[PDB]
Image (cartoon, coloured by chain):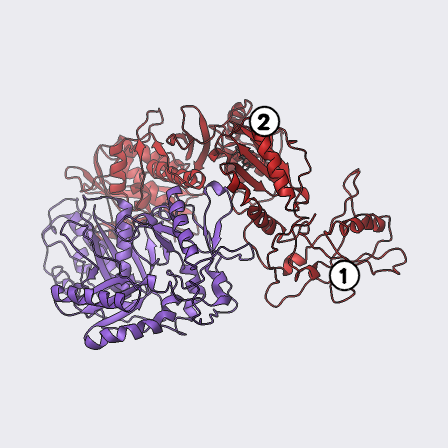
Chain colours: A purple, B red
């Protein structure tokens, strides 16, 4: 049904035309699924095929977000955003609650299906153009364009911002000590009450939502070993750490001392004022390796002294909203990985480790993907911004498989590290 | 014959106007050669004479081809295409024959004046204005204007294509399963019906199109069975590139060499084995197509090694989804690998090659994997599917690779295969330092400006050594120093370094690198029993480095 509701005229940053991104080749199964989805949406008036006059485009993908059964239609609006939303980052930006992080428990739930009913500016749909790729370039692409509000887009929830707040009041009222942030198709809700009491308050909001509109928060269902029920429950209470960790035992041989000092010299680049000379002096003798050499006096003063500087470190812990967040992950153990987020080199905002039960699915890629996603949400909460990921993998490899384990509505900007970092330690950071 | 099809809306680039080019007249027989066409084109409705209003001009040309009996004209919209908006990439991608389904009968129709039948936006017509003054330039009032798609205009391809796709829409409905592919001025229709039963539907289609203003000149079939599309030669059950002849000179240039490589690579699709490692390695020089590049001994043994295959014709099969897909990869050496994809044994579907160029020293495994990639990507692009991989590699060797390497990857279904060039890891550096092995603290450098360096070492057991070097880099030194440390060492050794650079290359566990030295080092690394390696700061670093570098510096 065509809704007579009025739209909001959308004008991006002049001197910057619409997106003309390249549609990655997809699996047959993937294209057909997308065809299904689209054909359905086409009926739902949501989208409409276009002609050649529309030269713009946008990537599309097939995900299995729900619980790996039905296909979700992911859309890479990473460009359109830059093109519009970055000027609608102020022109309609949603402020971030700097306490959300200080919270004790947070839950994320989809609310993308919300904008589907809302109409889109007439003089702008063109830019929403996306294409379903034909196998082996058989026929040209199947071209459509959103007549309503796009899910993947950032300018969508911005507009829905109004209608959202309004619907939120009733809950925000009866429940004041509950924070709510709206980043794209998702709503993050934070509470300080225990899980049980908290989980119930959720179904509440879930139900409340379904009450005030066809806004249907995708249902509950178990999955992993310790049986869950619903919602991605995050706990920013423990969102902190110092993954440094020095050898509490292995500090006897030359090598143990050798390799040690090297890391410490890299640490210089981060934590300032780290004395190792008194220590490095104990090896200057070109002595034989593996020789079990005990620690001296004046050298022992450089060990404990700088071992406490790593426990409590603060200096320039400033986050610049002007600058962008950069997160680079590095493969470590057979299951563990390490991420470091900063905006300026060595000025580490948040360092964290990741690891997926090495056994259920010891997939190299799967992990990375998962990690990327987790690292992302972590920032959203903490800064309400998506980092540019420096990914340690092959450009092509990724553009082939990320969409295989991608369980998010959003797609962060990424780069690929083709360089081996000697920064790989037992427990590495950046 | 115009088309009643809905013309798509066309406009100019933001705040831009149509071309205005009062072309210089030509009182030649050419001036009349035009009216012959225009006053028979306007008759056919293609164009129309417009009032002396605002319509701005565009260059006209009444030229005719060499001895062309039909004196046909041609107008070039070079400036117009500048003003007109951007359309959708008509033929962005290209369909590769290797991913087609074998059809019993096929026929190709000529859609020449196809563009001349499709109408043009009623509001864009005015931009196509053109004029033609006669003799004494006393009658310039011979201005026309296009109504259909102008030949050589910007939108003509995208639109037409678009229009056409919409024109076939209803036809492939009343009788689906009939494969119809359009390309520029071509229409490749293919169906699995007997010649007669097949030729039936064809005439249907023709009349169908005929009812849409578009006409098919050729009565039924005219295009001979062996088709030539983008070089590709097409046949009902096979495909190849019939014409693939590369001449032999004695002193060619870059201009000729690039083309040679071009043709060779083109042939890589089917002709299995075709290599270009050395054949291209020489183009590395400052591009100057008119500069003659002296053939090398290897370049000789390669071209000849290539011609060997190219001299004899080989074909490729088609796709049959019902059967599974498979591809096998094999190493050729010097960073050159070759792959073949097929469904039925020796029923080659397609082949190709991958090469790690411009870069140097890389693991054999990294490549095999990189290879898998190029293919995977290609498989999907063509069949939209991932093939079962048949590759020469032990699971164990591979496992330890991804477990040890830093960059993350993923190689789907793959099975082992046997072939002399068995890919493997010949060595592995000791994780933990060796207890009963000599230690070789090493150092090296060079007076960057003088180009003369010094490499050497010192051991736990005061076994020093130093060797001067000239005409080398600071890096070549750091490496040389290790080769030494290896040479004069025993079976199991521990080596310490000050170069992060030197450290890497080795850990990469590469092999067969064009770098002579690296090879001399690799071979050492293979012979050895155990080998540990560590790294420490270059300058302010001690552990011995505080005396090993003070020993290798003398001159500046
Ligand atoms: C995408 C496609 O079907 C296509 C693309 C380029 C060319 C030259 C012919 C094409 N199809 C034709 C056809 N009418 O089906 C074709 C096939 Cl399917 C197999 C072998 C020869 C031929 Cl001519």
Q: Answer yes or no: do the residues labelled 1 and 2 have beta carbons within 8 Å?
A: no
The quadrant of the picture occupied by the N terminus of chain A is bottom left
Mark linked to residue A330: none
The quadrant of the picture occupied by the C terminus of chain A is bottom left
Decide: few, some or many residues near mark 1? Use Cα within 10 Å; few <14, some 14-19, many ≥20.
some
Q: Are marks 1 and 2 on the same chain?
A: yes
Q: Is residue B372 visible?
A: yes
Decide: few, some or many residues near mark 2? Use Cα within 10 Å; few <14, some 14-19, many ≥20.
few
In the image, A214 versus B36, the foreground residue is A214
Residue that numbered label 1 is attached to: B50
Residue at the right extreme? Answer: B136
Residue B215 left/right relative to A212: right
At which x and y percent is residue B455? 33, 43
Q: Is mark 1 on a helix, strand or loop?
A: loop
Residue A298 left/right relative to B17: left
Q: How far apart are marks 1 and 2 (CA)?
A: 49 Å
Quadrant for ligand 1 reads top right
Mark linked to residue B196: 2
């Amino acid at each position: 049904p065509i809704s007579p509701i009025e739209t909001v005229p959308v004008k991006l940053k002049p001197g910057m035309d619409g997106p003309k991104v390249k549609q990655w080749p997809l699996t047959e199964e993937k294209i057909k699924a997308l065809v299904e989805i689209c054909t359905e949406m086409e009926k739902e008036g949501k989208i409409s095929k276009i002609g050649p006059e529309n030269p713009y485009n946008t990537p599309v993908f097939a995900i299995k977000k729900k619980d790996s059964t039905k296909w979700r239609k992911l859309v890479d609006f990473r460009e359109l955003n830059k093109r519009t939303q970055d000027f609608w980052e102020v022109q309609l930006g949603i402020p971030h609650p700097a306490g959300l992080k200080k919270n004790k428990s947070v839950t994320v739930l989809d609310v993308g299906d919300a904008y589907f009913s809302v109409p889109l500016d007439e003089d702008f749909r063109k830019y929403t153009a996306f294409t379903i790729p034909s196998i082996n370039n058989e026929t040209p692409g199947i071209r459509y364009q959103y007549n309503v509000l796009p899910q993947g887009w950032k300018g969508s929830p911005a507009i829905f911002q109004s209608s959202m707040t309004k619907i939120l009041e009733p809950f925000k009222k009866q429940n004041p000590d509950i924070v709510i942030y709206q980043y794209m198709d998702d709503l993050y809700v934070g509470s300080d009450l225990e899980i049980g009491q908290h989980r119930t308050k959720i179904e509440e909001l879930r139900q409340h939502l379904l009450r005030w509109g066809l806004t249907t928060p995708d249902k509950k269902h178990q999955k992993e070993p310790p049986f869950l029920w619903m919602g991605y429950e995050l706990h920013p209470d423990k969102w902190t750490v110092q993954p440094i960790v020095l050898p509490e035992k292995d500090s006897w041989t030359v090598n143990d001392i050798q390799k040690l000092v090297g890391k410490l010299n890299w640490a210089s680049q981060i934590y300032p004022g780290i004395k190792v000379r008194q220590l490095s002096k104990l090896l200057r003798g070109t002595k034989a390796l593996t020789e079990v050499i005990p620690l001296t006096e004046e050298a022992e003063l450089e060990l404990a002294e700088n071992r406490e500087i790593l426990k409590e470190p603060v200096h320039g812990v400033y986050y610049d909203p002007s600058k962008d967040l950069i997160a680079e992950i590095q493969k470590q153990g057979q299951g563990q990985w390490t991420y470091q987020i900063y905006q300026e080199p060595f000025k580490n905002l948040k360092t964290g480790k990741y690891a997926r039960m090495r056994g259920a699915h010891t997939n190299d890629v799967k992990q990375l993907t998962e990690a990327v996603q987790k690292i992302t949400t972590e920032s959203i909460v903490i800064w309400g911004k998506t980092p540019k990921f420096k990914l340690p993998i092959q450009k092509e490899t990724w553009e082939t498989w990320w969409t295989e384990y991608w369980q998010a509505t959003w797609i962060p900007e990424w780069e690929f590290v083709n360089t081996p970092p000697l920064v790989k330690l037992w427990y590495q950071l950046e | 014959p115009i088309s009643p099809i809905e013309t798509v809306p066309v406009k100019l680039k933001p705040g831009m106007d149509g071309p205005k080019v009062k072309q210089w007249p030509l009182t030649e027989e050419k001036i009349k050669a035009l009216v012959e066409i225009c006053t028979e084109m306007e008759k056919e409705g293609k164009i129309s004479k417009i009032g002396p209003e605002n319509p701005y001009n565009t260059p006209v040309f009444a030229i005719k081809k060499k001895d062309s009996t039909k004196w046909r004209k041609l107008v070039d919209f070079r400036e117009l295409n500048k003003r007109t908006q951007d359309f959708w990439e008509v033929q962005l991608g290209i369909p590769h024959p290797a991913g087609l389904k074998k059809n019993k009968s096929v026929t190709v129709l000529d859609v020449g004046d196809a563009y001349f039948s499709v109408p043009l936006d009623e509001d864009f017509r005015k931009y196509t204005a053109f004029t033609i003054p006669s003799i004494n330039n006393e009658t310039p009032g011979i201005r026309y204007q296009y109504n259909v798609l102008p030949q050589g205009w910007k939108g003509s391809p995208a639109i037409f294509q678009s229009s056409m796709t919409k024109i076939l829409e209803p036809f492939k409905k009343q009788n689906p399963d009939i494969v119809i592919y359009q390309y520029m001025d071509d229409l490749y229709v293919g169906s699995d019906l007997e010649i007669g039963q097949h030729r039936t539907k064809i005439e249907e289609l023709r009349q169908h199109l005929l009812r849409w203003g578009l006409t098919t000149p050729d009565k039924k079939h005219q295009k001979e069975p062996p088709f030539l599309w983008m070089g590709y030669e097409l046949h009902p059950d096979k495909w190849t590139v019939q014409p693939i002849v590369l001449p032999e000179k004695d002193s060619w240039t870059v201009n000729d060499i690039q083309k040679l490589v071009g043709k060779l690579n083109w042939a890589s699709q089917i002709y299995p084995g075709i290599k270009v490692r050395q054949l291209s390695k020489l183009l590395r020089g400052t591009k100057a197509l008119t500069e003659v590049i002296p053939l090398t001994e290897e370049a000789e043994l390669e071209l000849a090694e290539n011609r060997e295959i190219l001299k004899e014709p080989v074909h490729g099969v088609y796709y049959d989804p019902s059967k599974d897909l498979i591809a096998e990869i094999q190493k050729q050496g010097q960073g050159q690998w070759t792959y073949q994809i097929y469904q039925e044994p020796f029923k080659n579907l397609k082949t190709g090659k991958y090469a790690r160029m411009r870069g140097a020293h890389t693991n054999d495994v990294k490549q095999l994997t990189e290879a898998v990639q190029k293919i995977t990507t290609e498989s999907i692009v063509i069949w939209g599917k991932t093939p079962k991989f048949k590759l020469p590699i032990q699971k164990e060797t591979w496992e330890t690779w991804w477990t040890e390497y830093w960059q993350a990857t993923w190689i789907p279904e793959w099975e082992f295969v046997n072939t002399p060039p068995l890919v493997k890891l010949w060595y592995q550096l000791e994780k933990e330092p060796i207890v009963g092995a000599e230690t070789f603290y090493v150092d090296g450098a060079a007076n960057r400006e003088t180009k003369l360096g010094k490499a050497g070492y010192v051991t736990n057991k005061g076994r020093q050594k130093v060797v001067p070097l000239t005409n080398t880099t600071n890096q070549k030194t750091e490496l040389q120093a290790i080769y030494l440390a290896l040479q004069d060492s025993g079976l199991e050794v521990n080596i310490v370094t000050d170069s992060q650079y030197a450290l890497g290359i080795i850990q990469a566990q590469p092999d067969k690198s064009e770098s002579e030295l690296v090879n001399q080092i690799i071979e050492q690394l293979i012979k050895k029993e155990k080998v540990y390696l560590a790294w420490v700061p270059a300058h302010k670093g001690i552990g011995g480095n505080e005396q090993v570098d003070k020993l290798v510096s003398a001159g500046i």
